[PDB]
Structure formats: structure tokens, C-alpha cells
Length: 160
Image 1 (cartoon, rainbow, N blue to C red):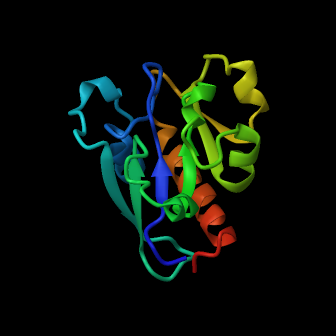
Image 2: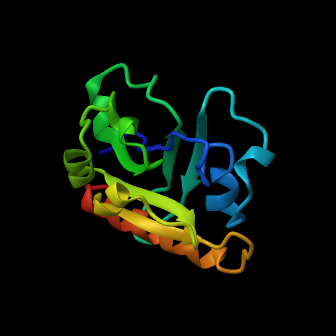
Image 3: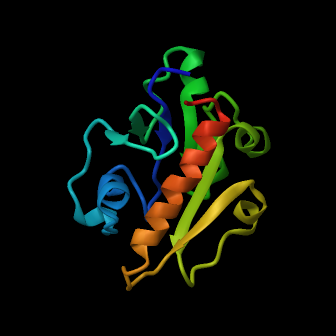
């Protein structure tokens, strides 16, 4: 696949990662409360990543909505989905049940250490990732691990 891959990150009130704070997190390994940053009017951010195990840099389109999906083939480009924990998140997705969706797209569920994971989310085939509420010294490693996790997924989906 050669078009830019897509990461879906819609948000709910409880979301700890949204399009508003995802760049700071993934590029600077700096976690910031998303309500304390400028909103992103179009719900779209771009991030370029140079992976160790992929030759060319990869440019991600990271969106909080599915308005860009004007042809079904856009859905084939979705390589990761951040989940809010609401099952209604997927209602308008090409694959709208979590079982099918997370069999073919990598899912993540981020939450604060100490906060319980909803039972239905625990059952989903998504990777649960914890962040400290009040310490930030682990963030560098969490982000390194996230990128490694995503790199592995890209290689498996044929990105070279």
C-alpha cells in the first residue's frame, strides 16, 4: 500500500488522547490534558514518522471523524483505531462490529493507571495502554513502545 495510512481517533469526554494532544504525545513524548490545548477545527492532524524498519518516511493522516471516507477504499488505509470505550463508536465504520473490525485493524485503548477498563472493552481485541495520571517519566517509553507496536502492524499490513 502506497497512499498515506490513516489513524482514527474520535473522542469522548473521557478520552485521554485526542487529535488535540496526539502530536505532542507521539512526537514529543509529552502528555498534556487535551482540554488545555487548542482545538483542531477540521479534526485532522498529520504526523510523519521515520521508522527504523521501513525505508521511506510514513505520513499519517490522523482524524477524529470519518468525513474523508468518500470511497470505501479509504477504509483499507486505516491502520490503527483509538477507542473511546463506546460501542457506538463503530456504527458508521465499514466494519461496524468490534470483532470484525479489530481482526483486521489494530485497536488501542488508552487509560490512566488506576481507572478500570469497562468489561466490554476488556473483551475487545485491542491493546490496553496505561498512562500515569500525575507522573510523566514513563511517557518516553510508552511512546517508544507505541511506535514499535504500530511499526510491527504496518510491516504486517505490507508497508515496506
